Structure formats: structure tokens, C-alpha cells
Image (tube, rainbow, N blue to C red; front, side, top):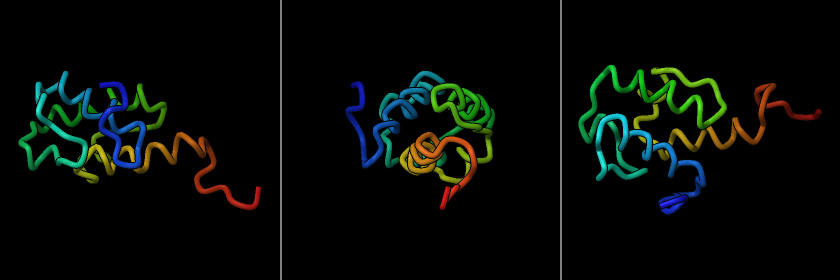
Length: 92
């Protein structure tokens, strides 16, 4: 479902959709955790750089491992996507 599951992130719905294709976890939700649902270490690597494409943001294994959930991934991504470059550039 296009942007069906969106817990305050319109993006998070594409993130788990990748994991469904990568690992095959169809019953993986956005607020659910990869590692809590059972994830394979190399698939985090694949996922990360897969997400990097659809996010347009620099994503490596570190981030998908740290946030644990695609909800918390989209949480930072949507902000990085909105702000673009120059991290936290205030008083522009």
C-alpha cells in the first residue's frame, strides 16, 4: 500500500517495503524492529544502501542497525530529505 503505514512519516512505508523484498518479511511493520523480528547481518548491509537510493540520503549499515526500526529510520530520513545538505543549518 503506497504510504499506507505512516506513523508520522510518509517515507517509512517505502522502507519496510524494501525489507519485504530483501529478506522476504511481508509481515514486517514500520514500528517493528528488524532484529527483533529476526534479521540477517548482511541484509542490513543490503538494506542500508538500498534505502540510500530511495531516500536520496547517505545510508550505511550503521543507521539501519542503530535505529532498529524503519519508523525511526524514516524519522531521521524525512528530516535529512527536507533539510537537504548542511546539517541543522539554522539562521541561514
